[PDB]
């Protein structure tokens, strides 16, 4: 009733990477290594790098799923709030209830789990292009952390899993997410709070 969040590189050395976007007031997405936390604006591009030490088999996939970080909320499905699930901002593929979308991948699939009712979005794993050392998935988060009746100011984690063609686990990584109006200021504030 709760997905695992244990980091697991697995046989292929799977792990995530993030750009170094800084903390200017204007930044739309920024990652804090010290907090393992992504700060982003609503429905803005969040580039997440996928790194492996060796290429997994054809048919490998990469799944993203959100869970609440606090234990007393972890059994609750993370979903869009009653406002945003009705605002008709569909990309033609993502169900309007799903918090996490993938941008610009026509092979993305959206799952409503028939047993847990949790949402996820999955894409094929592909090796890096010629001259590149990793691949990047562009995610969008479609509600604010503060949305009433949805996340309701509760922190969430995103769990990224590398899966074989049957859905079996090959690798796992994760990061906290805050969706907010001013990611640069909020990253600076929370990093200062950690230091203090
Ligand atoms: Zn919302």
Image (cartoon, helix red, strand yellow):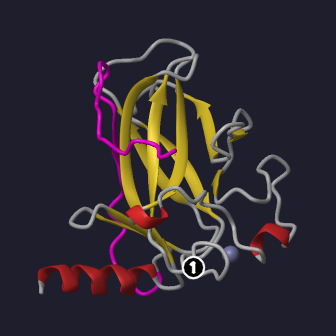
Dominant SS of magenta comes to: loop
Q: Residue furthest top?
A: 57
| Residue 183, horizontal then vertical, whole percent | 44, 79
Q: Is residue 125 in the magenta section?
A: no
Task: Work out whether residue 71 can be spotted.
Answer: yes
Query: Which residue sits at x=62%, y=44%?
Result: 120
Asked if 124 appears above or below 57 in the picture, the reply is below
Left-right relation of 102 to 11 = right
Query: Which quadrant would residue 166 be assigned to in this image?
Result: top right
Asked if 56 appears above or below 70 in the picture, the reply is above
In this rendered view, identify the residue nearer to me: 148 or 116.
Answer: 116
Q: Residues within 10 Å of mark 1 (few under 14, many from 20)?
A: few
Find the magenta span and give its range. 1-26
Query: Which residue sits at x=64%, y=68%?
Result: 43
| Callout count | 1
Query: Which quadrant would residue 176 be assigned to in this image?
Result: bottom left
Does the residue tagged 1 have its C-beta within 8 Å of any atom of ligand 1? no
| Residue 146, horizontal then vertical, whole percent | 56, 82
Q: Tag 1, which secondary structure?
A: loop
Task: Work out whether residue 129 can be spotted.
Answer: no
Query: Which residue sits at x=48%, y=74%?
Result: 154
Judged from the image, the quadrant occupied by ligand 1 is bottom right
Query: Which residue sits at x=26%, y=67%?
Result: 35
Name the residue beneath numbered marker 1.
152
| Residue 93, horizontal then vertical, whole percent | 81, 46
């Amino acid at each position: 009733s709760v997905p695992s969040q244990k980091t697991y590189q697995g046989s292929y050395g799977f792990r995530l990477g993030f750009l170094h976007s800084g903390t200017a007031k204007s930044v739309t997405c920024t990652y804090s290594p010290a907090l393992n936390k992504l700060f982003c604006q609503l429905a803005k591009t969040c580039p997440v790098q996928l790194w492996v030490d060796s290429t997994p088999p054809p048919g490998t996939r990469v799944r993203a799923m959100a869970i609440y970080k606090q234990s007393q909320h972890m059994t609750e499905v993370v979903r869009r709030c009653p406002h945003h699930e009705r605002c008709s901002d569909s990309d033609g593929l993502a169900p309007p209830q799903h918090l996490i979308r993938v941008e610009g991948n026509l092979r993305a699939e959206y799952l409503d789990d028939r047993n847990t009712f949790r949402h996820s979005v999955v894409v094929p794993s592909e090796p890096p292009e010629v001259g590149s050392d990793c691949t990047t998935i562009h995610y969008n988060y479609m509600c604010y952390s503060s949305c009433m009746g949805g996340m309701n100011r509760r922190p969430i984690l995103t769990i990224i899993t590398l899966e074989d063609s049957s859905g079996n686990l090959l690798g796992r990584d994760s990061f906290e997410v805050r969706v907010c109006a001013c990611p640069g200021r909020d990253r600076r504030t929370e990093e200062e709070n950690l230091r203090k």
